Image (cartoon, rainbow, N blue to C red):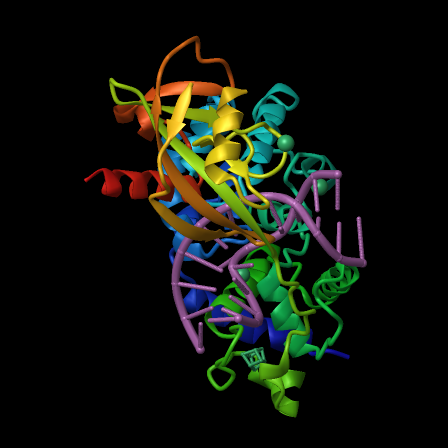
Length: 350
DNA sequence: AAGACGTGGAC
DNA sequence: GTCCAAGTCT
Ligand code: SF4
Ligand SMILES: [Ca+2]
Ligand SMILES: [Ca+2]
Ligand SMILES: [Ca+2]
């Protein structure tokens, strides 16, 4: 049916030739491949590079990561987004240490039982690190295959991914699955790009139904995103006389879990300074807002308003709250939105 | 199934 | 503005 060998040859030769020397490609420690694959979920290669370098310098092996304090691991992820990824990884390595004594399982089902490890990450890690011939279908590979085999199913359905997964097993080169899997990923990065794909340069120009029919720009097929809710948020930056600032740790469930923030209130309607004033009551005086700005998430947009305030100590500071010397805020992991809050507060203070 | 879950860069 | 970023949990 499908000229697998001729296809594989023009792909893998292209790949030994064009492969980028990325940091996590220096070797095949499963730990390092695994860390990189988690960081790369919904995140551009170029963004990941500096975080990977710093993360592995802090946590050079699996037990280092497991032994480390949740707070330390989260701070190393600060700014990357989708922070549940690193809680899942941390939990997952703790389990690989206790349960399996430090060795990354090479059994798919056992590896996949670990938190964070879905079908993509099973494929990527096991095919690169241990040679296991599982497909590693990322969003890019779904685009590639959609264009190659002219598969028009919505790639948002879980079922479509399962179809693409089966296709990969058929066309795969079981002689070297790691390189096969990498090469498809690399092809989507370097040639078969979301817009204006470089089909003329493409190595597998000859096997591409979409190019033949002239529709590469028309793929892949994906349901248009839903518009996201908007959420007004009042944020208090409260300083006492010695310059200390009040922060609090978000709970471990839901949005931006276990990250630190300046005390904040979702103000569906009005009464920002009021709804804020009452929440810290549950001794503070808040002045007029100093800035308003938006911050996007995938599924909502915060509309933040920052209110300065003076803190007067009439009691102890009870969890989740913490009294932080300004010079110590850098120790805590904050979301990018509250990083900006602080920046805006300090430039107003000038 | 399809919503929750961050952030940034290239059109 | 849109689409994607080497997805996964619920
Ligand atoms: S010929 Fe174009 S559309 Fe087909 S795989 Fe190559 S870059 Fe993608
Ligand atoms: Ca799994
Ligand atoms: Ca919660
Ligand atoms: Ca990709």
